Length: 69
Length: 116
Image 1: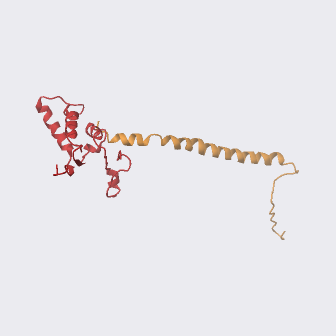
Image 2 (image 1 turned 135 degrees about the horizontal axis):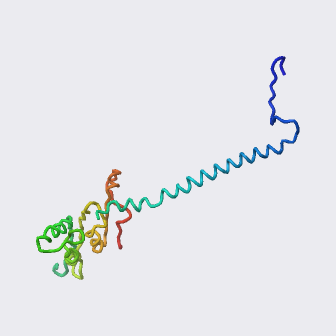
């Protein structure tokens, strides 16, 4: 507290009236973990699959260049 | 045969038998002959075998032969190299990409093999 300014450095500062926000903090955690799940899926499912796919049979084609027939 | 002995160790060196093959190609059409699957003389296999068979170390003497093998268009699947492997116990193959890397010599480790 200062004669004009007050700062509140709270660990967990939540706009609320009652100590019952447990119903919304879990919702926040589920949102974060769900978006993490989206990250893990779309990074893996898109790339890692396509990572293997794009590298399928390159040398098979590279050797059959020098075929003059 | 050496007196009280046999023939000696024979050093033989072939310089692009592919040239001989190429000449056989050159002549075949004029010979009234037909065109192989690419254009070679059909008789190319038998003539190559005839050529190779008179080349051997026998009960008499030892003959050591080195063969220069040009590879047309740098292709293995050409009929002539293919036939050639059926003739060479010692196979040594070169690459263009290895030389493209500046490595001199540029022999490929893999395909060059030896029954020894």
